[PDB]
Image 1 (cartoon, one colour):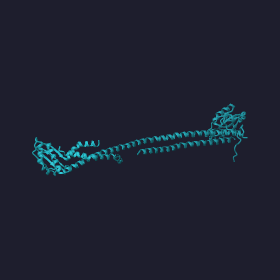
Image 2 (cartoon, chains in turn red, orange, blue):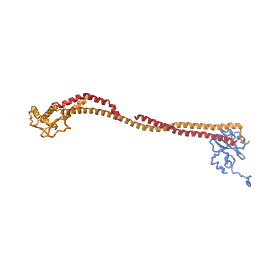
Image 3 (tube, one colour):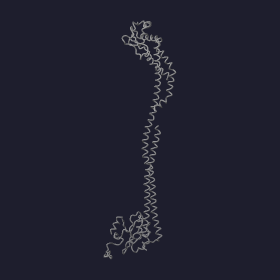
Image 4 (spheres, chains in turn orange, brown, red):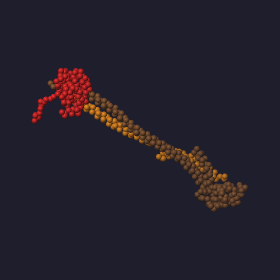
Length: 97
Length: 223
Length: 121
């Protein structure tokens, strides 16, 4: 039973080694997962910052139309006092000194 | 009888099981620590990898943002200037149409000979009184020379009544006629030495009137 | 075939008793637990009058001793040499406990290259 009792313990050690090696495989997986779950966290933050940049990133016709109400009142005051101004200028020019 | 022991086959198995139990237990605990530390390292490393790159992304974002925050207000500035320019250039396009009609009206007066004749006289007399020279040269439109010749006497009469202190010997109507395109009426009077001229044309008088009237009109219309 | 050799050999004393002599000519590779994280083998030289005691007490000289793992390796006129398998962390406890019972633990720090060299005999 000398070489039989030992064989039992050696088998237990072999089983123990698998347990530890499995945990080492776990760690190895866990370390790659860090690189994976960070690469997914990064390009989602990249597209998100790009998203909120393009939202911010938002034409002479709009400058004329923006003042078409003033360009209309200018000709308005023009049509009224026109004939009364022209009348004075004419009289002034042809007046016998 | 070949095994050296003081224990029953059951006893040796109780002790043999007890040892291989310890071995496995020692392995479970060792493995437990490994995967517990791996979980901690996973979090640490994931965070770091992320923070490395987020600091990079944040950097060029704020530069791109500031860049776009500048172009955003460059347009706001350029639009608000195009607006103030259109307004100003419209105020002028209107005033320069008031004076434009005024000078069409002036041409209309010149083509009414019965209305223009007394005006032309007063324009010629006023000019001669600014000269006060014994001989005066009169430049006029080619279409006015026949009219002017037929009122030389009335002109020399009216002049004598207003300037006895500086008599007028003769009026010379120059054959160098005024330009149809520049002049609609009036005359240009100069002395013989050609050192002095009085431009008393309708266009010139209005031009001089503009000097003071244009700001005045601009003030009363668009104060 | 395999005959014509002297199986009855006359040998002379080249060493002292089992408690002090070199053991390279006495022990075989199979007497030792090799390449184990927990297990190792100790040799104990026991005076013949204490042979009985060792047999029924070695399994309790220290904790973590492999039960029924003892075997007789050799014997002379004064001593019997045993081997015992146990946990490395209990060897110090074991050797001390053995000395107290007037046994004599034989130091023999074997390695894998110091036992593969033993197969050359």
